[PDB]
Image (spheres, grey):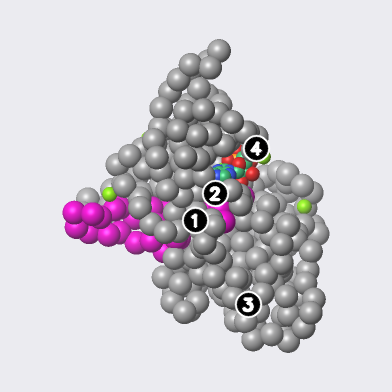
Amino acid sequence: ITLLECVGKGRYGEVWRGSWENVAVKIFSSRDEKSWFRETELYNTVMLRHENILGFIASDMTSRHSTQLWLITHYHEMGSLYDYLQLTTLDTVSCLRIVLSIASGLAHLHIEIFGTQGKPAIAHRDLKSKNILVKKNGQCCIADLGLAVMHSQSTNQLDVGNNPRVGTKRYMAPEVLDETIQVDCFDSYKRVDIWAFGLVLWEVARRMVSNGIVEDYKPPFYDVVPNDPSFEDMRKVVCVDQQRPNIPNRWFSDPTLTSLAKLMKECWYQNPSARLTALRIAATLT
Ligand SMILES: Nc1ncnc2c1ncn2[C@@H]1O[C@H](COP(=O)(O)OP(=O)(O)NP(=O)(O)O)[C@@H](O)[C@H]1O
Ligand SMILES: [Mg+2]
Ligand SMILES: [Mg+2]
Ligand SMILES: [Mg+2]
Ligand SMILES: [Mg+2]
Ligand SMILES: [Mg+2]
Ligand SMILES: [Mg+2]
Ligand SMILES: [Mg+2]
Ligand SMILES: [Mg+2]
């Protein structure tokens, strides 16, 4: 495989555009061996084939001067939803196309499929606009299963891995931050994905035009925490002071943003049990 154009760095590795046609090649720091392992575990055994999930190609360890860990996936030339939202504006058609496709990806991860072509129930745990890619057909796929937890109904076995990495601090649910999440109950990881999905929903809705105007792209809690907030930083905002992103008033002059602020509402309850499910979100968006 021919590494051609690097397209990013990160806190855990780097991503290249290579050929083998075009493929993406994430190259992990060996300080992040556990994420490469976990991701390679899920893709090679769960067989995750779905429109709204980053398709997988292969996984290997090679040369390069030294023993780098490669995860080779479908290349999407339009990149992250995060970079996409800072470049472009959305209308009604492209914005619903995007939040629905994310919702169906998260739902398909969250439900256990039984049968030959089945899968366990999977919770993402680091969902964010940088971990969603936009592909050249309107849909988006979810990526980075490095922290994924799995649950199999047949055994009631919860499988959380041994990755010491924690999710992106900005998108953490309050139960994660105050450290009262039930670690034994798989559903609480599903409710962590929903909280972050609500944040992503706010990110996307801002960039949808209505009555001729938009908001600039901003990351969640942009107005109250610094770039790269730390653990204690987000704790003050989400748990103690109980802050949520603000709804622009111009959403109440459009019926779509009306019912998009409807959803975010019901992913943001601090009590995680009250939060919507990805199936319910995906149902509502249809
Ligand atoms: N399959 C892919 N196709 C195209 N671009 C991709 C792909 N996977 C990742 N990227 C982009 O490559 C860049 C490198 O990012 P990456 O190292 O994967 O994580 P990140 O963007 O830094 N987010 P984070 O892991 O939270 O730090 C980002 O701009 C990604 O959007
Ligand atoms: Mg980067
Ligand atoms: Mg399977
Ligand atoms: Mg990533
Ligand atoms: Mg990514
Ligand atoms: Mg991935
Ligand atoms: Mg990873
Ligand atoms: Mg493991
Ligand atoms: Mg900020």
Badge 2: residue crowd in 10 Å (few <14, some 14–19, many ≥20): some
User: Pointers 2 and 1 in contact (CB under 8 A)?
Assistant: yes
Asked if residue 167 lies left or right of residue 185, the reply is: right
* Mark-to-mark CA distance, 1 and 3: 19 Å
Q: Earlier in the sequence, mark 2 or mark 4?
A: 4
Badge 4: residue crowd in 10 Å (few <14, some 14–19, many ≥20): few
* Mark-to-mark CA distance, 2 and 4: 13 Å
Q: Earlier in the sequence, mark 4 or mark 3?
A: 4
Q: Looking at the picture, how far across and down is residue 201, in whole percent?
A: 61, 66
* Mark-to-mark CA distance, 1 and 4: 18 Å
* Mark-to-mark CA distance, 3 and 2: 23 Å
User: Pointers 1 and 3 in contact (CB under 8 A)?
Assistant: no
Which residues make up the magenta segment?
105-134
> Is residue 144 something that shows in the picture?
no
**For mark 4, what is the residue?**
8
Q: Earlier in the sequence, mark 2 or mark 1?
A: 2
Q: Earlier in the sequence, mark 3 or mark 2?
A: 2
Badge 3: residue crowd in 10 Å (few <14, some 14–19, many ≥20): some
Say which mark, if any, is on residue 141. 1
Residue 51 in magenta stretch: no
Most extreme residue toward the left, as rendered? Answer: 116
**For mark 3, what is the residue?**
92
